[PDB]
């Protein structure tokens, strides 16, 4: 598929562009960390935040009194998700690069006003990180739900760029004696570290070990 | 110190704020990956990009013809640098969290128009990733320098937020029988992978193994 809109048409390095939903979803599903762009207080602020996908929308949360959740009401935003996958070492400095996956989602986000729906989405967020976890926790209080904003944005107006594989040098540079290659980069998760305030008689759910990213 | 400006004053979770330049520099020095916010084509786009610090400014590069480099001359931007350091598992869903380091730099970026200065800064970028690397490469062409933009932004108008350590539950939840703790997260660098097209007698510089992040 071509780009979904003129404003999502990748121009630079367009050979790296992907617009298909399989790729959009695969990148969104690989990581929890987004960066949301929104005009606030005169600046295109970039807010790091967690996000989760359900079908054709992504969601994020924060304070019901938070400035982003008010500011997103009347402007189109950009939600960017990036993964750095390697440093690409070429024979010329100009052709150094990185391997990566990134997606930009554009458009008008909306807040979930229905508190029952909001709680259902927040359960999906938690259980998407750690299966079954929401049900193990101290039961949520109504005031906690009501203090939380949940925003969502369609994934439809999305552009991706992906780079994999070796360096690509100018054809005339392959006789130059310098070492080229790739340094792979990834997220690593380490074993869980228990809170020292845990009750000694409380087991660790095995599901905690299923959390992964990158 | 307090915030350097009203627009960098952390309000939410203000106890996590840091404004001291030692913390600003330590976060900036830990990672090459930034996200730059800039209003372009009616959207506060969030562009992932590499950056490097020299003293009291950060720098980034791209095409001399790139839209970001044109747009930054006439608006204040936000440059955000985030590091995800762990998933914080609490007894209540409301107090789940993450350990992290993040810095936002605000203000008016500047382009380097002097080609000789630009080339000097680009060598600092490369050798900041891999010591001694620039010298090893196929010598740079004037046209390569001239095709590149380099922008910079002062680090002075900066806010940081940092979270470390265990979960912090409501005090009344500490008798609830659920496991709390932290899943640490970090970047990992893997062994370098040579380009198959490397010349057979050209060894990998040991300095490649010095590249690190996170
Ligand atoms: C980990 C990482 C590191 C990077 N480092 C650098 C760097 O140091 N220097 C540099 O110049 N660029 C870097 N890039 C690429 C950068 O994000 C931009 O893609 C590039 O600079 C072109 O931006 P542009 O606005 O000129 O693109 P244009 O092609 O003019 O943008 C047109 C449209 O393309 C789409 N698009 C553009 N970039 C992306 C993207 N990254 N992901 C998804 N859709 C996109 C958007 O819909 C956008 O509106 C990096 C990307 C990643 C993920
Ligand atoms: C890895 C990571 C994941 C996160 N996940 C979430 C999430 O899922 N939900 C959530 O609500 N928040 C999340 N945060 C925090 C988020 O980035 C914001 O700090 C928070 O949402 C409050 O934003 P605000 O605009 O309401 O802050 P305000 O306090 O109103 O912002 C005022 C000023 O504080 C400064 N500031 C705000 N946030 C930051 C920051 N992160 N770093 C540096 N300076 C800052 C800026 O100068 C800003 O202009 C995450 C942060 C990181 C780094
Ligand atoms: C795995 C799940 C979750 C993670 C990783 C997470 C992470 C975060 C982070 C990082 C912040 C920002 C705090 C700061 O400013 O430093 C935040 C804020 C917030 N979260 Fe969550 N959260 C999770 C689940 C939830 C749930 C399920 C709820 C509601 C039941 C919730 C309610 C809130 C609220 C209300 C805020 C704003 C706090 C304030 O500034 O007053 N969170 N969360
Ligand atoms: C370690 C060093 C470097 C890294 C990691 C790096 C990375 C990148 C990345 C990721 C892009 C974006 C390409 C895309 O759109 O997918 C880029 C673009 C660019 N880089 Fe670099 N780069 C490095 C060094 C340099 C140097 C030293 C020069 C100049 C000598 C240079 C010149 C350019 C130019 C001109 C572009 C724009 C290309 C275009 O779209 O026309 N880069 N770089």
Image (tube, coloured by chain):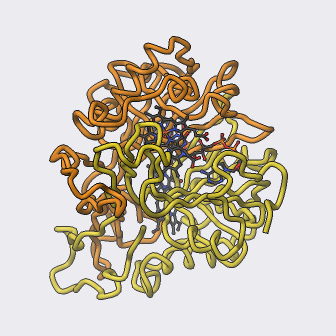
Chain colours: A orange, B yellow
Which corner quadrant of the image does residue B27 belong to? bottom right
Q: Position of residue B118 (x, y in %)?
A: 66, 71
- Residue A168 visible, this orientation: no
| Quarter of the image where the C terminus of chain B is located | bottom left
Q: Position of residue B124 (x, y in %)?
A: 57, 79
Q: Is A140 or B76 nearer to us in this picture?
A: A140
Q: Is residue A111 above or below residue A193?
A: above
**Left or right position of B119 against B195:** right
Residue drawn 52% across and 54% down? B49
Q: Is residue A67 above or below residue A56?
A: below
Label count reads 0
Q: Position of residue A24 (x, y in %)?
A: 34, 30
Q: Is residue B133 above or below residue A113?
A: below
Residue drawn 47% across and 79% down? B139
Q: Position of residue B208 (x, y in %)?
A: 33, 80
**Left or right position of A46 against B111:** left
- Residue A20 visible, this orientation: yes
Q: Is A166 or A185 nearer to us in this picture?
A: A185
| Quarter of the image where the N terminus of chain B is located | bottom right
Q: Is residue A91 above or below residue A113?
A: below
Q: Is B129 or A125 nearer to us in this picture?
A: A125
**Left or right position of A121 against B51:** left
**Left or right position of B148 against B70:** left
Q: Is A102 or A65 nearer to us in this picture?
A: A65
Residue drawn 47% across and 53% down? B168
Residue drawn 43% across and 23% down? A3
């Amino acid at each position: 598929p071509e780009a979904p809109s003129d404003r999502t048409h990748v121009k630079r390095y367009h050979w790296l562009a992907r617009y298909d939903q399989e790729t959009v979803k695969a990148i969104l599903d690989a990581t929890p960390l987004a960066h949301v762009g929104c005009m606030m207080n005169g600046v295109p602020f970039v807010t790091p935040t967690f996000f989760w996908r359900e079908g054709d929308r992504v969601y994020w949360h924060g304070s019901s009194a938070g400035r982003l959740f008010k500011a997103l009401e009347h402007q189109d935003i950009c939600l960017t998700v990036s993964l750095l996958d390697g440093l690409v070492i070429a024979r010329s400095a100009y052709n150094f690069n990185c391997n990566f996956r990134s997606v930009m989602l554009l458009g008008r986000a909306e807040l979930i006003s229905d508190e029952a729906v909001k709680a259902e989405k927040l359960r999906n967020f938690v259980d998407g990180l750690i299966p079954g976890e929401w049900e193990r926790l101290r039961p949520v209080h109504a005031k906690e739900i009501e203090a939380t904003a949940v925003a969502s944005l369609s994934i439809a107006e999305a552009s991706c760029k992906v780079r994999t594989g070796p360096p690509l040098d100018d054809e005339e540079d392959y006789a130059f004696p310098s070492w080229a290659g790739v340094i792979p980069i990834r997220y690593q998760v380490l074993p869980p570290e228990p809170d020292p305030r845990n009750l000694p008689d409380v087991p660790m759910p095995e599901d905690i070990l299923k959390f992964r990213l990158g």
